[PDB]
Image (cartoon, rainbow, N blue to C red; front, side, top):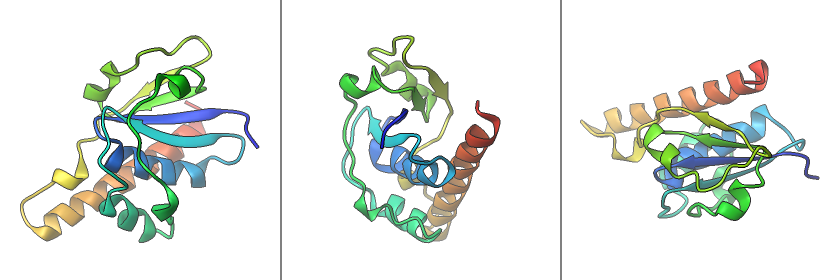
Length: 139
């Protein structure tokens, strides 16, 4: 069914929004519809898939898109997963609200492969924590 809409938004859909969507489906429920947008997209990032799938959250079925004001303006909520992304809110009437975080893009983490992967693990854990707080606190 449908009852609310939550629309993730980041500087690239491909990474942060895709993972936030997978955690939100666990922490929320059918009382909401959960999708992702971004300033841009490139694809369902293999990191976003494997990071969620290692938690048992098979986001392989998801897809990326760039922002569409036609869903944004109807959402109960828009979640601007990084502050530089929050500029890209073309219309959020009183039917909508916004939330804000500061997540750097995990696919660009670097130092060594294990440091890049560790950064993937940190970002999923914090995004999952974010949805846990949002769900529990009703922020």
